[PDB]
Amino acid sequence: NAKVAVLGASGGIGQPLSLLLKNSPLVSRLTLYDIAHTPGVAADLSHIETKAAVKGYLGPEQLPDCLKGCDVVVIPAGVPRKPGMTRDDLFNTNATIVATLTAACAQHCPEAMICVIANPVNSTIPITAEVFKKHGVYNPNKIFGVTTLDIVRANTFVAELKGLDPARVNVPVIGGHAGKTIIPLISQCTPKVDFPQDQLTALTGRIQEAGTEVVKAKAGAGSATLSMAYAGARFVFSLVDAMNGKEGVVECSFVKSQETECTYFSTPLLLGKKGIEKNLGIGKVSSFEEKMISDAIPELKASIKKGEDFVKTL
Amino acid sequence: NAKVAVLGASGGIGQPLSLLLKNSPLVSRLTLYDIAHTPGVAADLSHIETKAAVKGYLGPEQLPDCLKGCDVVVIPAGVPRKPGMTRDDLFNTNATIVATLTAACAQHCPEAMICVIANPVNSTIPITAEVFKKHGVYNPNKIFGVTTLDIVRANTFVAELKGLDPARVNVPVIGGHAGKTIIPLISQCTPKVDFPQDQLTALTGRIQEAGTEVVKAKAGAGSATLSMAYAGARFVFSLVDAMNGKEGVVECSFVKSQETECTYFSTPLLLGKKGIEKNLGIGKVSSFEEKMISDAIPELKASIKKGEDFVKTL
Amino acid sequence: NAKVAVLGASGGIGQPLSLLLKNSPLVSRLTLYDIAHTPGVAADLSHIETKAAVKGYLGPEQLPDCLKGCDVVVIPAGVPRKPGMTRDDLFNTNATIVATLTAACAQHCPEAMICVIANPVNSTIPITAEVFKKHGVYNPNKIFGVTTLDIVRANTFVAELKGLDPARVNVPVIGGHAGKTIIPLISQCTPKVDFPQDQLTALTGRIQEAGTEVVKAKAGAGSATLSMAYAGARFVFSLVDAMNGKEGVVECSFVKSQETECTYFSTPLLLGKKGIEKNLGIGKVSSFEEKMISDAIPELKASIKKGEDFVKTL
Amino acid sequence: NAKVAVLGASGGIGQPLSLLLKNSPLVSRLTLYDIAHTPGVAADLSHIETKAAVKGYLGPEQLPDCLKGCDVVVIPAGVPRKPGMTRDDLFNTNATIVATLTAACAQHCPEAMICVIANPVNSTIPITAEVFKKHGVYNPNKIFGVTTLDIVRANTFVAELKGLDPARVNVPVIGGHAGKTIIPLISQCTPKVDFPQDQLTALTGRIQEAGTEVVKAKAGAGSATLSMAYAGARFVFSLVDAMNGKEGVVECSFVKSQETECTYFSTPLLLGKKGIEKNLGIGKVSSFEEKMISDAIPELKASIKKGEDFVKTL
């Protein structure tokens, strides 16, 4: 079974994400990293009656030990938004956080699956790749920008409008994770759904700005933590099931891609033992959906460039 | 199709508990109450792709709306311990919180299952019962002091020592929830385990002081939260399974009892459609376990009387 | 010339108290101790344009370095109250904190003035004294329970009612620091003030419950911090000035005594180079005030015994 | 008889600031505003034996009552930096906070002195000015960006290197408050000091990034709070002294200026009853200092226009 490392385990996302991972029979070893509180979070989780052995590591001195033999590394670490902030306002802090932590992964568990939640994902994935490139252990099949929350939100909002059980809805979401770059493919939704354009546009904008909606609702107490923990655990479970030989596992994720002109893009991915087995690509989309893909590419390029430029300055 | 209310849903226990409940197909409605942050927590959780309708309530005016029509109310509300404190040290603050919240339950959802997590459970359950008596709606088959975390700990520690799958381990734990009153019935464990005496003594002590162990490890940042969320969720699920007619559902819980001279006591309970179907009692125990029961009684009685006396000062 | 150590410098009282000490011409060196955040606190304060050299220490291993050569040790360390709690609810944690910290003082700066702010003062001073006795380093003229806040409050409340400037009001307060052990001597007030018995009783009760009123006003966010830092600073400045040879320095403080049948009591103290120069005693009091002293004695003796018995068990 | 309002009085800066203001004989009315905790902060502070009347206000509804008849308004409200953030990263959040609070000032106490601590000061003072203009109550003599912490730091560092008492050191700092816009005029220091060129660049670098060093030293637990409180208090005292007719009070502050190409600039100001009595200007500076001024102007203009643009789209 899998050894999973959580970098930033003591934060708002990290604690409940670590709880969901500990509850899973797919995990046998769970290592927790942060700069504060980890030993306490680990002692807490270690009492839970599941097989996953839990250990907390504190400070960069113990970071190498945390990473040894890891099959998957999830990185919820990062500063959350306050009302008013854009995801780009977090770029500077989260870029150096992701740069520092992915360097440690490249040095200590370069063969591991790397799942980045830290925002803005549209720049932090490029950063992760370039950091891995500079260490000479670059593998684009094992680096994932976790955009799963966008799919989870689309499913819920569609299900609510159509009176369906969200657990049986699937809405592909492509592009990236910002405004802007979030493209819900309602045309490719299962079960098949039918919305008027004004209702479709409202639904689309709702999915696009759902992160901001939660920031407003929290009124300065941060951004999505619990739903983000759910989405992160879902993606890790999908990846680990696939690594154990489960067939047909498809998740959208922001990865190194030659699907569009963007070197990085989020599409549905067939997962497996090497990570990305096959990029299933964008597929058949509406004219409305195609317009969005075109409007988003400009921003994606900037975000990719910004992230790549940041690594060169190091 | 269960409707569940969480009173204290914005706290360290409450948030991860609410996440676990939201993730469950047993829950169709999840109402969250606190004095702060509930709208943000509910907005966060409402995005998760499960059927449970989530709503946040804030302030005294909204508490009745939160409770109306509930099948189960879980009360993690309360102040946590710091290193050096006993659970009894929290009595004066948490007794008032439990009194107020359980009074609201007696008025607005008297038929619901009331699950009290707030410590010290040995006194706050007596408070809850007396509050329900005052409102003329006391049903001892529906008031539960959640001691599940002790069983979860016992399962984990037994499994670690013997090298077992803790999912397969069930250790009955009786008495109450405070240092000396926690009595692990290792002799009644399934699968049956034999420990040499020195391991048995260290194991029993470890279970009894497990809560203090986590408080120490957290070093001033509170008590167990994530494992208490796990334990609380587990107990709610067992209760909901029983209400849906599932047979053979057994959980230990601190309830109104006849087993000893203590009017409240924790034993294994067969659960059913109206809560406690049958108190299975203490059963056959070792001499060592019998001695531990004898030692627990005076402290239990003292904690029980304290709770009763507090209600008489209201 | 004075070197002052602050034990608990990162806490709610500790940070503002450290700020006030940093701003004083009397302090040459300011060492700050805590189990978290001290380096950031020391760095923050070291930027202030005063002569005191500031350094932050972190964890028990660095406590000896923090204490070496200290002239005055201030101990604001400890857990604050939440609404509902009494000061004795903090006993178990704050007793353990005080016994540990004062044991380090007795070893590493036995000659220093020990100013204890940690509550309950009526027990924590007896604890401090017993720890110094156990190390064979007894000086009852150097151990102070900081009750200054009671005098500060009394001054303010009298001043508000009579329309005076609180800066020019002085009210001796004797006894201890908990509920009815707080005995303000309004008869000895300067300037002379005329209160009828009904207003006198209201004013006295206000002074006695002032700490509880702040806890209620803070509604879960702790106890008095800023006013406590002010009073702690005032007492440390008075003590240091007396150590500089300043004449006629008098402050009420809870110390080991033989003024009443309590072996510990707060009275006006003439301070000097060796700490307590002379205990000025109670002086002449009204009948109302004599009754309060008599009613206070049972509670004080019990708190003293509780504190002393705590050290003997360790 | 100065009435002082503190907007953001419950924050890390606001609480110790409010304490220092409460301790001063210059203040007669102290009104505290925030969105949480102010009643408790005011209760705490109201016990201190000084004459300042203290009142806590809570939420936008009580903001007019807080500001009514104020002579000075100090605004420490704002999100603090975490390691890796620039002050400009805080812009979107803090620009909204400042625009809201200053609009209320313009509506309810338009003749008061407005002192903004909220970062980035280089943009937030322009926001304040434009907001006041939009209400037609613009007075450039009464709006102050509090840069005093830069001077306090410069004094301390100079004094440390030269073995001087920092209380009797004065180093003018000009420009703005962000990165290279901080320009310490070591050539104008009193007493006169000579530094070799290598030390001067190091000394200048230390002063420029001093805020960042405290952020890193706090390692995620915020930015400077206690030194900022000290600096905020110093500036308010200077300004209040001058309003009572005290002569020769000089402070550097980021104000509306015609001293450079920039609309706003920090230089030594002579303060008076009207606020800015006279802008004392940059004065004679070295070639090194002239170079820094030249390099800084492009960044200052950008920050200025950014803040102006923000208000122009409300």
Image: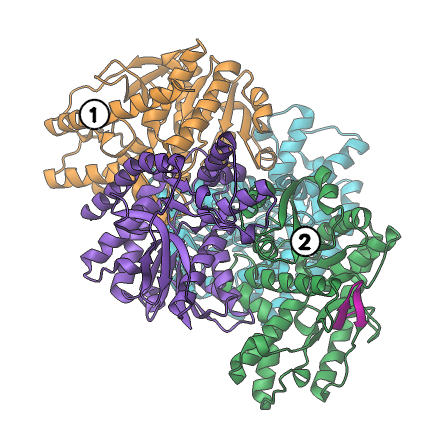
Chain colours: A purple, B green, C cyan, D orange
Circle 1 chain: D
- Residue A181 visible in rendering: yes
Which residue is nearer to you in this view: C212 or A117? A117
Secondary structure of the residue carrying tag 1 is helix
Q: Residue B83 location, x and y as percent? A: 56, 62
Q: Residue D304 location, x and y as percent? A: 30, 22
Q: Would you name the residue on which mark 1 appears?
A: D298
Q: Residue D308 location, x and y as percent? A: 34, 19
Q: Residue at x 46, y 35 (%)?
A: A205
Most frequent secondary structure within the magenta stretch: strand
Vertical relation: C95 (above or below) A231: below
Q: Residue at x 86, y 55 (%)?
A: B133
Which residue is nearer to you in this view: C275 or A87? A87
Q: Residue B103 location, x and y as percent? A: 79, 49
Disc 1 crowd rating (10 Å Cα; few below 14, some 14-19, many 20+) is few
Q: Is residue C22 left or right of residue A102?
A: right
Quadrant position of the N terminus of chain A in the picture: bottom left
Residue furthest top in the image: D136
Vertical relation: A248 (above or below) C166: below
Numbered range of the magenta stretch: B265-278
Label of residue B39 in the image: none
Label of residue C259 in the image: 2
Which residue is nearer to you in this view: C90 or D26? C90
Q: Is residue A42 left or right of residue B1?
A: left
Q: Residue at x 76, y 68 (%)?
A: B271
Q: Residue at x 10, y 38 (%)?
A: D197
Q: Is residue D185 left or right of residue D36?
A: left
Residue B268 is covered by the magenta coloring: yes
- The answer for how far apart the CA atoms under marks 2 and 1 are is 73 Å
Q: Is residue C144 left or right of residue B66?
A: left
